[PDB]
Length: 118
Length: 122
Ligand SMILES: [Zn+2]
Ligand SMILES: [Zn+2]
Ligand SMILES: [Zn+2]
Ligand SMILES: [Zn+2]
Ligand SMILES: [Zn+2]
Ligand SMILES: [Zn+2]
Ligand SMILES: [Zn+2]
Ligand SMILES: [Zn+2]
Ligand SMILES: [Zn+2]
Image 1: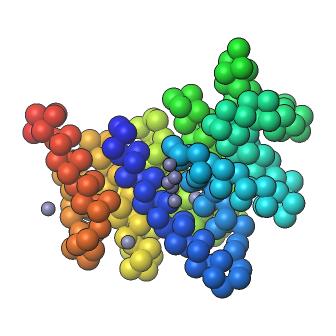
Image 2: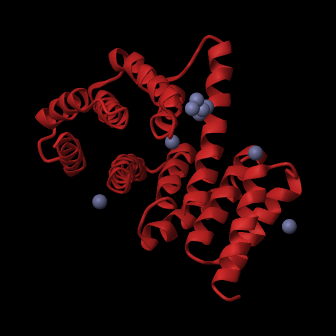
């Protein structure tokens, strides 16, 4: 239920933030640590987490491989979709559908963005 | 959020499945990859995925360090809670509370398990 979703999310966000702030103090944030931190931020209920999570994914975009960039663009569309930036979230998932046309998860996300605009 | 949570779950579950199957074909499966896959499995909508995630966590339990074992025990309690293995979920969350008495997440999880048992008539 909602209480269980809150418990697991708090456990993950508390661990990933502590791991992110520790590597940031050491001047060496790995891409996995920054991605998992932004992954929890874009799934948060509050906008100042979603905005922060989108910023972290934008920084990882010019530093990841083509397979890693697809996972970043997917959650950039998810993050902007939850910030009601529907037009920007569409160009992210459409550009993702150009390289993976048969991605059922990305194709279904386009439906949510389209139904939100309509 | 219902359709959106389904999308994020399948996207992560498919990504870590391929990374798990690739390392499995290589012979060696790292603890980080096996944990991340099991972490998504115990959070899936379907029960068969949750059971597979519990098995992967049971294999990592005797291997990991004391800090890694706390995360294994925490999600072993979450997985068994969703499968309504209540007494099994209690022994895990009570074991984590033995080493961390001030863990509000495990303390609230123990109350959640207790509520679900009374709602189910046990
Ligand atoms: Zn936070
Ligand atoms: Zn707020
Ligand atoms: Zn906040
Ligand atoms: Zn806030
Ligand atoms: Zn927050
Ligand atoms: Zn498959
Ligand atoms: Zn992860
Ligand atoms: Zn702990
Ligand atoms: Zn107790």
